[PDB]
Length: 430
DNA sequence: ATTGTGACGCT
DNA sequence: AGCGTCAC
Ligand SMILES: Nc1ncnc2c1ncn2[C@H]1C[C@H](O)[C@@H](COP(=O)(O)NP(=O)(O)OP(=O)(O)O)O1
Ligand SMILES: [Mg+2]
Ligand SMILES: [Mg+2]
Image 1: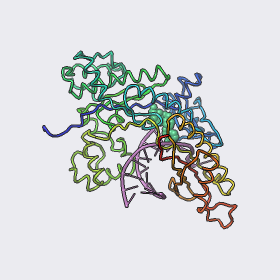
Image 2: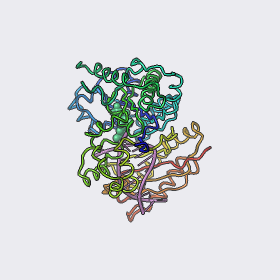
Image 3: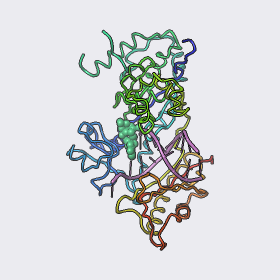
Image 4: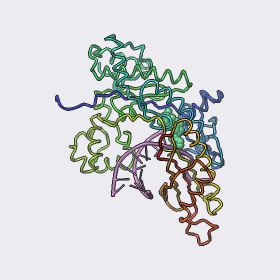
């Protein structure tokens, strides 16, 4: 009752770019706009691998991971843009730079946590208080929320999508208690107003559209964001959680999409997030550990404490290449040449990072995968990163991995290498 | 023959 | 440190 905290202390948003790499390519090439199109990596094997899909193409069943030749079977008019290739490998620089455009705009409004190349969490608690005191008890007009959905509404006692959106928004705004600067629902609503402004700024200043979730924590904000993609934002209130979670598959919640979530389902014999409420905290800790158990106990009630971390920049800079099937590396000169290619791309990125961000990486991580290993990475080893020099970095990487060659003759490499990876980490101010 | 990333937990 | 999980 009076002492059960409800996880309503913060306003958190998650902003996620719509079909991001496609929008980057559509901005550059107007011929691709408003078309079924996808972004592909490589081309020789089965037309290349799709990594991003416009919503028009999704209507035909085109998905990420699909080979372009197969996507063309579903959508013969599908347009394609290829990822740039440099030093024999896909190079993601255009999309990293477009990401920086977006992240810098978001940072004007509040502290952000860069969660991926196309999404960031925003802690809007302080901006909301500021806007509430600036408002001074004035009601919030539906005109300030032109792309907002209120999850769970309309309910209780039109057949077009926009009409239903507005009905739900009207119900929400009519029930709002604007006199209380401490009402969590009012705080979320003001947060949604700010996120409308943020998303309008992103679109105006970059051309890119995005979706967003607004709630009281990161997990609910991320879940909310997906409910009404594309080009829309969704408010998930604390009160909306019991109905929303009552039919929400456990795998849809961030961090439960893999083996842990499958074990929750298997061990407890449940399917939906809401069913977790019927277990004690101790029961959940007994099955999934102290940390996971406490997290699940609170999360299924809509409560999570994970902070929005003040971090706009990636904390590692990595370069990797797969060598699948018959292309696996089997000679010493091959391994050396590709380590050099990776190191040269890495040195380029690291030198730019040092100039832009006043920091230097101090550790080099070298990872490989050998033919036959089902795991993604076979061995990882670190060494010192003291100079941004590609030849030195590639020589050091080879020195670190050379004992992995089981071949008697040095000139060959056994077993063949199906992946190389160089990662710069452990950044220090400079 | 997904690929190229990137954050964080465990021991 | 080196390995595993999870999601982009
Ligand atoms: N498995 C993968 N491998 C490589 N690149 C990937 C990838 N998954 C995504 N990307 C790249 C390409 C993606 O554009 C970008 C952001 O990933 P999302 O936010 O998961 N997906 P998007 O923004 O395309 O669509 P929407 O958010 O509207 O559903 O990261
Ligand atoms: Mg996205
Ligand atoms: Mg994303």
